[PDB]
Structures are given as structure tokens and as C-alpha cells.
Image (spheres, coloured by chain):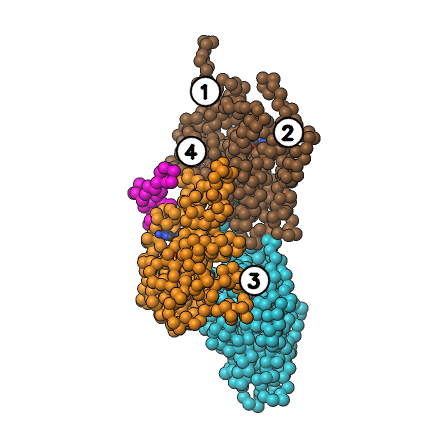
Chain colours: A cyan, B brown, C orange
Amino acid sequence: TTALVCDNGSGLVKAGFAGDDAPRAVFPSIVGRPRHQGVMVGMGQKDSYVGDEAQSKRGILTLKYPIEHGIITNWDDMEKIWHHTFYNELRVAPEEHPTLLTEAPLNPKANREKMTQIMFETFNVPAMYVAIQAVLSLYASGRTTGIVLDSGDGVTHNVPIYEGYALPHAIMRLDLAGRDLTDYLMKILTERGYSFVTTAEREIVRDIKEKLCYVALDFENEMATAASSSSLEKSYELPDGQVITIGNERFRCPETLFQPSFIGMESAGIHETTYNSIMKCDIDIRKDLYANNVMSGGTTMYPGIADRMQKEITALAPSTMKIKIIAPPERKYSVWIGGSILASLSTFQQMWITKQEYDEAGPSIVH
Amino acid sequence: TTALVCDNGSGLVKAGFAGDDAPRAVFPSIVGRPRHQGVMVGMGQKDSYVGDEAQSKRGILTLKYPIEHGIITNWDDMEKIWHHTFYNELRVAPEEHPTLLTEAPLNPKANREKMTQIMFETFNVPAMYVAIQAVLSLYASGRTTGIVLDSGDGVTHNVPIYEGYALPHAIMRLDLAGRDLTDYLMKILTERGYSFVTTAEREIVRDIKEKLCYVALDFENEMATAASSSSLEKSYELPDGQVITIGNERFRCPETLFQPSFIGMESAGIHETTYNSIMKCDIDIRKDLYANNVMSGGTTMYPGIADRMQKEITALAPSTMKIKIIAPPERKYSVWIGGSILASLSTFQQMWITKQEYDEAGPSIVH
Amino acid sequence: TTALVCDNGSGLVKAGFAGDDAPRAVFPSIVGRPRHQGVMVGMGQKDSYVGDEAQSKRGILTLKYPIEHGIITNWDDMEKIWHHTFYNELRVAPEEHPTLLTEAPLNPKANREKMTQIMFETFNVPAMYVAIQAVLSLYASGRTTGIVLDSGDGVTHNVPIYEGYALPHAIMRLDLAGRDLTDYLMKILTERGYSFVTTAEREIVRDIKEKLCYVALDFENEMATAASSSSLEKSYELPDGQVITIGNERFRCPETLFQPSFIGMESAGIHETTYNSIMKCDIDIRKDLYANNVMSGGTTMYPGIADRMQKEITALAPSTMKIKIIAPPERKYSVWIGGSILASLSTFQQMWITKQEYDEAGPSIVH
Ligand SMILES: Nc1ncnc2c1ncn2[C@@H]1O[C@H](COP(=O)(O)OP(=O)(O)O)[C@@H](O)[C@H]1O
Ligand SMILES: Nc1ncnc2c1ncn2[C@@H]1O[C@H](COP(=O)(O)OP(=O)(O)O)[C@@H](O)[C@H]1O
Ligand SMILES: Nc1ncnc2c1ncn2[C@@H]1O[C@H](COP(=O)(O)OP(=O)(O)O)[C@@H](O)[C@H]1O
Ligand SMILES: [Mg+2]
Ligand SMILES: [Mg+2]
Ligand SMILES: [Mg+2]
């Protein structure tokens, strides 16, 4: 009956039935084993904690993110993520619903095969399909044309779609935002004598990466008044009681995303990968990619975009073109709000890969 | 059969079966041989008197404490303590019950083996285990987080614990309180012209260390009003009828522990060893070590602590952090009431070292 | 006039003019004030002794290293270090030369500014520059490619360099060896019944860390032969006439630098940090990072590396890729013999930060 949209984020895995409100459960993609000797003898502990509870047990575990640079490390950790998601969040049996899974646009073969095969044999679902996360972000703002910028930890993408076809030859995948921003924040906060090295404490870096950062309009000129002894200091409080005063590094960390040359890699800035994906599309269609520029994903929630992005695009594109960048509030749930629209609707009600078809065809059902 | 918790005090050896009230026997850990020439000729007097009988025969013996600086001096005296303890207090044979023994956290190797080994061949016990005295103090107050203190005459320890694991990197052992406080009390009672030198009479010094002593809120401000003519004098009476009036030195002796520069040693104050053991724990756990500071051991019974310790820590700790320091009645028996809770409980009924397994393994069994 | 290279040791300050032999003066940085009351009104006693004289007057002082966890404690003690170093060792006046100072590759900013500024106002030197300690280790063995190690009591570092560019993305800082090895030797020597707790005596432990330790080739098998009566026992003689017999623990203390699991801290050994810095470098260059592995410092002077390090890396590295590990003699003076080659060579004779430029610009001239 009711289909299930379960999003394999690298965040922030999101789980909720098909429509109509919001993700039922969201928690960080963490499994963590206990690194210290037991001496109270309940015994009372698990062999492996998942999140939320692996984020309540900080400082006693060794956190292992099972998805790293756009790929899952091994399915031994992945199945334990899955077991936690179905059972102590959604509560429903896996044999009850057809499921809908998400992937990253341009993900390595044979990691969709191996996934599909393992998931059928481990949880015994009755039907399934895998839709890519960028394409789904079209549905959330309900547009049939435009270039989609879907940016989440740890893979961003630039996919062009026109009424309502996706060009296979103009899709760009960057392995950059947001975990490299997390690692960079840890590298420029060490620069003020605040050292973070332990895995649990690495989460604190994420919590200040969320809340306290912002982006400039013109970097060099916002940087200029930062050099003056004028306040940009906001004072954060740390869990053990420590008080940190950051100012410069606060706008510096997300600004890193414009120009990967700050980490020295040859990769082009979001400025130019957006533009170069548009300029791999056909000449006539370019007219309508402007003003259907749609940003998405959780790593676009800094309170200093899109007007940085705006000022940058308007400078690089042709003269007198209508360029408005549509960025809805609460971009982090865009993908899920996509998935919800698909699986609740017909036509695609008769289009899942069903069990008899899977048994007959085998795991080689890629296209 | 019911288990036996027999606690290897540094005091004050304590003995009583597992559960549920108080130890049956507590008495000074002393052996004393008769030093003066014999003339009564009944005769039959014992070669070595143990406590408490060696404390009702003061002035005719030469007391030799079998435990000094937290380690047992020789097993010739120790076996006579043991034989006396089981037989002439409890009235039971060690063959009947599994035992539970205690140690000092960070006790020199190879003195846990030789102990374990000698006890199997001397008393023919069916099973045993050795738990460290600091860890056991958690059970007494039902804590699942917090820093634990076994402070006895004369080895103290400082162990931080988080639910329900031990931290190898945060544990500190001081060979400071309390026998050096006794020896210091005898050295500063010489300052008022009352000189004591004999071992047996040293016990009287311990008895005034118990009853008369107290700690200040602020040393310097109690010291100021001590210089005034107003009375802090309490009049003690001595075993042969003599009257001593001490006042200034009365609050000075336990105050010595708050910074042992009085002795001359470089060793840090309890104030700071408490704090510095906390700042060797992981950052997110520190939040809950504050306000689960639980004191223990008989040597913490001076009336002025813990509110000296409280006022001192709140000054050294980060701003606006909650620090409730827990120190109720029962602290002299804290460790033992801990041991009682363990040996009655399952799972740990199957976790004693039993004789066949010992026979196979040998005395190399530690870890 | 000839420039002066004075190396701001983590240890262990080294001082000597630009080239070409060895440093004139080496001593382990300690300052010690006199802690007991004077009883000879002679008296002649200085307020602060530096080393050598503060290592001759052990047991009546409280030794304080001015550089702790890779940063100077405060400039009140540091300025007295400096004044002693230039004046009462090297004899030359700072007013007569450009000087050359060393730093860590990654260290709290702006404590390189404050340093540079205070040193200019206190000693009023004609010109200066601050070079990182890791880069200089290339010069010492005349390498044009390779990964550099400054490991001193207590900062290690891992910097990859390619002819003659430094790669920012791959620089890794470990706050691991060697003072935590000093603390670890003190923590496992209490396990054999010899206690060392007071400040002066802590130096003696450090001296036994120098001479008698060694690293195993195969850990598991060295542990096997330790359990038998097969002698690995060496007899040390101790300052007050005492005899120390160490076996197993002799190889246990340095083994800590592999596998930080022994302390429980979340980090990976030199084995893995070497690899993890290489696999953060661009693909083509990796070919010459293998076989230009250059070890350095004083805390790599154990007589059981590098062929352990080699056998371990060779197992983890890609198959049939040749890996030479070059550890020269002289490693304690590596940094200094590096600095010496640079400051004697033009072109960089005209590139010191000079007084007129400093006076106009202020502390920001650092970058
Ligand atoms: N307000 C915010 N500002 C900046 N970054 C944020 C904010 N909220 C969340 N993030 C980042 O966004 C990430 C979540 O992105 P998400 O949309 O879940 O990506 P995915 O769906 O691919 O997992 C988190 O890792 C977090 O670091
Ligand atoms: N009321 C008191 N005030 C101060 N000290 C006391 C008091 N009662 C006992 N003590 C001291 O505490 C010691 C006993 O401590 P205890 O908890 O038995 O240590 P352990 O268990 O390690 O032997 C005795 O040596 C005695 O000097
Ligand atoms: N033969 C040796 N074996 C092991 N360690 C040594 C030896 N000689 C010196 N050390 C250690 O090396 C340290 C000195 O390292 P050094 O190169 O001076 O570091 P830095 O230059 O950063 O101060 C000393 O603290 C000492 O403990
Ligand atoms: Mg995504
Ligand atoms: Mg005790
Ligand atoms: Mg160094």
C-alpha cells in the first residue's frame, strides 16, 4: 500500500513514508564501537551503537561514517544502519511496503548492482527502485526545466534538465562539499590553538559548521574590513565549559568553496562548474536554463548565499540575460520532498522492479 | 555458598560476608611482639598479638604495620593477619566460600601474583578475584559516571569513570594521605612541648587525628582569626591522666593536605590532581564529570571537607559550570559496601577465578 | 656579519652560528626556582637557574619546561631563557647579527606574531626570520623530494615536499611523541615498583628514555620471548646508588609510538600517518614520495627503527613499489645543520625581515 522513501544521504539519512509532510527520522550517518575497557559490569552495552544514540555517547566510542567520498565503505556496516532505520525509527516490517532508494548522480558501477542484490537478499522487500538525488530536487520546487545544483555532504552535483529530459553529456559531479569543508574548518580552527583530533569531537566541528558560519558578497572587500580591529567575534561555548571567540575564520571556511585552489586542487569553483555545465548544453536551450537556476541540499544553508552566487554568475554570463537564482527555504529536505511526490503518484505506481521480475532477471537489471 | 568480601585496608582491614549491612570485623592492621623481659611465668603468651588485642596492650609491644606506602611488607606477618582474620573474627574456614579481595589501584607488579599465589597454597580457597578499591566506590552511591577517591592511611587514588568503562589515560595515584598526616601531627605536636616517640603511643596520635581535627573554608582567613586571642582550644585527656590544650595546630594538621608545601614535596594539591585527572579525559565526557564528583575513603571524614574542596574547584573550573560534590555519611565503609553489592549479583557469579582454571593457567594470570 | 641560528627546541634548545660543524650549546630548556628555605646566609643564589646549572642543581628546585605541548608557556620565563642563551653561552651580542629562529610547521597563530614582536622589542636585533623545523630536514641530507619528520619532546609532524614545493593539503600534525613517551615510561616503571613523582626526578626518567630503550621488529614475537626466562634484562644503576632491573618494559615504552591504542587516544601510528600524508598528495608525485622517506629529530633515535618502519610500510604500500627509508646518523642536529646551509647561502642573504621594514609594517609582516 503506502510506499517508503528512505534516503541514503551522507548526512543525515532521512526516512519517512511517501508524502505528505516531512522526514520522520533524521540522524547522522554514524556507527561507533566502544574503545575503552568495561568495569561496571551491567554489562548493558551494544557491540555497535548507531545514531541518535551514537551521538549521545560521545567520547567513549570510535565513530565510523559508513559513506565516505560518495561511496559506502562495506555492506557489513551498511546493513546495521539499515536495521536501525527500519526497526527503531519507522517500526514497519520490510516485507510490508515497496521501497524507494536514492543514490548519488554518477556513482561507480557496480555499486548499484551489489547494493540492489544485497538489499533484496538481506531484507526481503517486495519491490524497489533507485532514483538519483539531483533529479528529485526538480520535483520539490515543481519546475520542468532548469539546471539543478544539489549540494550535500560529501558530494555536490550540477545536472541540467530541459522539459523534461536530462542531457547525459552535460552532467558534472564534484567530490568536494561538505566533508572537506568540515576538515578545512578543523584545519583553520587549529590555527587559533583549538585542537580537535578525536573522532567524537569532530562532530563539534560540524555543529559550528552549521550554525555560526556565513558567506560574504565580495570576499576580498569583506576580508579587508576583517583586517581592521572591528568586531566579527561571536563567542561560542563548548561542551566541557570552554569559551571560543572566532571572527575571521567564520566566513573564511565556506568561502573556500569558491576556488578549490584554497586547498590547491585543480578543480573549478562552483561559479565556473555551474556555468560550464550550462555551456555544455545546446545553444537554443541555454535561454531557458537562465532563471531556472535551482540550488538545493543541506550544504547550501549558509546565510550568505545565493547573492554571492548571483553576483558571480551575472558577471560571467552574457550581457542582459534574465538570471534569478531560486533557493527555497529548508533546502536540506529537498530530495525527500522529491521522493515523496514520485512514489505517492501514478503513473509510476506500476514501475517498480518487482520480486518475480527480479528473480527472473537477476541483479544485472541496471538500465 | 555465599561469598566473602574481605577488604585489604591500608588502615583497618575490614571483613564481612557478601551483603547487606556492615562489615563484621574492622580492626587496626598491627602485629606486636613483647619487647620487655618476662617475670610472671604462667606462661603461655602468644608469639604475636594481632589487633584489636594489640591495641589493648599498648606500651609493652613494638607495633609493626604490615602495610606501609600501600604495599604489604612481608608475607610472614601478612599470613598471620589473614589466619587471625578468618578464624578469630569471622569463625569460618576459607574452603567453604569464594572470596573477593581488594587492592590499591596502580599496585607494583609482581605483588598481585605472589599474593594471589600464596593465598591459594596457604588457605586452599575454592575461588577468588581482586578488584581495585577505587572502582568499587561507584556501587555504594549507585553512580554511572564520576571521579572515585580511595584515600586511606597512607595511599590515596584519583580515578575518573564514564558509563561503564575505565579510562587508562586518566588515572592518578598519590602516595600522600594519611600516614604522613599522622607523622606530621606528631611533628607539630612537638611544637607545643608534648613529645611522643614510641610506636605504641603513635596510636594515641591517630585517635586525636580522628576526633579533634577539622578543615577551614579559607585557610588564610581562619589563620588570621587564629592569631587573635579568641579560643579555638579543645582540651584533650591522655591515657595516664594528662591534659593537652591544642587550638592553632588543631585545624592546621588536615589543612596540610591542601598543598603539601608544608612537608616540602613538589607533589600537586588534591584541588589540582582532581582537576588535572579530569583534563586527561575526552572533551565531551568532561561535562558530566562536573557534578558527579564523588568522595570516598575514611580519611575524608574531617568536618570542613567537602565545602573547602567545593569552593576551591568552583574557582578553578570554567565559568558557569554546575559542580555538586557528593559526600554523604558511611564513607569509611564505602569500598566494602561496594564489594558487597558485587559478590551477591549475577552476571559475576561465573566470573571468579576458580581452582581448576588457576591450576591450568598458573600464577601468570593477571589480565 | 655571520648570521646566528638558534633553534627553539621542543626539547632541548640548540645554539650555534651559521654553519658548519655542530651547535655550540645544547641543554634541556628547564628553569628552576629554589623551593626550600635558606640556612646559609652566604648566599649567592640566583632567582632563576637555567640549564646546564638547573640540571646540576636537581632535587632542590622545581623544574619547569618553558615549551609544553608545542607552545611557550609565557614570555616572562622565555625572555630569561633567551637572555641566558645568547649571553651566557654564545657570548655574542644580538645587536651584531641577523638571527634565524625556528618554529613548528603548524602552530597557534598569532603566537608566531607575538613571539616575533616581543623578541624585536626585548633584544633589538638588526634582522630576523622564522623558518619551520620540518623543511630544514631536507637540506641536512641534500634531498630535492620527500616527506619530512620533526619529532621532538612533544611535537611530531608529517610534511610532504616535491622539488621544491610544499604541498599545503597534505601537512599532518601529531601531538604524540616524545614527552608522552616520557610520561609513559614513568607510568610503566611504577608497574615494576620504582616510583617517580616529583618534578626534579622526572629528568632521570627522560635520561633512561635516551640510552636504554629499543623498538622491536616483530612485536608479537618479542612479547612471546619476554614471558620466558630468556634474558632481555639489562641492569641500570641509579643516581643514589640503587639497582634497577628492566626486561619487557625496555621495548614497551618506544612501542607506544606505533598504535596509540596503548594510551587509548584516537589517532593512528607513525606507520599510518606516513601513508595518510602520502595518499593526500596528487597521483603522479606519489612515485617519488616512495623512496625519499626521510626520518629526523631526536625522538627517532631509538636503535630499532627504521627497518621496523620499513617492514610495516612495505606491507601496506601497493605491490612491488620500491620504498627506501633513509634515516641518517646526526638526526638530533638535523634541523640545525639544515638551517646552517640556508642562512649562509645567497640569494636569501637579502631576504631577512629587516628593522626599517618591521618598524613600518608591524607584526603582520610574518606572512
Ligand atoms: N545551517 C547550515 N549551514 C551550513 N551547513 C549546514 C547547515 N545545516 C546542515 N548543514 C550541513 O549539511 C549537511 C547535510 O546535508 P544533506 O542535505 O543531508 O546532504 P545529503 O542529503 O546528501 O546527506 C550536514 O553535513 C551539515 O554539515
Ligand atoms: N572521623 C575521622 N576524621 C579523620 N580521619 C579519620 C576519621 N575516622 C577515621 N579516620 C582515618 O581514616 C583511616 C581509615 O581509612 P580507611 O577508609 O580504612 O582506608 P583503607 O580502607 O584504605 O584502609 C584511619 O587511618 C584514620 O586515621
Ligand atoms: N638515543 C636516544 N634514544 C631515544 N630518544 C632520544 C635519544 N636521544 C635523545 N632522545 C630524545 O629526543 C629528544 C630531543 O629531540 P630534539 O631533536 O631535540 O627535538 P626538538 O629539536 O624538537 O627539541 C629528547 O627529549 C630525548 O628524550
Ligand atoms: Mg546527496
Ligand atoms: Mg584503600
Ligand atoms: Mg621540533
Do discs 4 and 1 belong to a common subunit?
yes
Label 1, residues with CA under 10 Å away: few <14, some 14-19, many ≥20:
some
Going by the numbered disc 4, the residue's amino acid type is Met
Residue B261: x %, y % from top left: 54, 39
Q: Residue at x 60, y 42 (%)?
A: B294
Between the C-alphas of marks 2 and 1, the distance is: 36 Å
Q: Which label's residue is closer to the chain start, 4 or 1?
A: 1
- Indicate the chain on which mark 4 is placed: B
Q: Disc 2 marks which residue? A: B247
Whether C225 is among the magenta residues is yes
- What residue does disc 4 label? B115
Hey, what amino acid is under mark 2?
Answer: Gly
Q: Nearer the viewer, mark 4 or mark 2?
A: 2
Instruction: Identify the residue position indicated by label 3 in the image.
Output: A205
- Which amino acid type is shown beneath numbered disc 3? Val
The numbered mark at residue B33 is 1
Please determine if labels 3 and 4 lie on a single subunit: no
**Discs 2 and 3 carry the same chain letter:** no
Query: Is there one chain holding both mark 4 and mark 2?
Result: yes
Asked if the beta carbon under badge 2 is closer than 8 A to the nearest atom of ligand 2, the reply is no
Mark 3–mark 1 distance (CA, rounded to whole Å): 67 Å
- Which contiguous range is marked in magenta? C221-249
Confirm or deny contact between disc 3 and disc 1 (CB under 8 A).
no
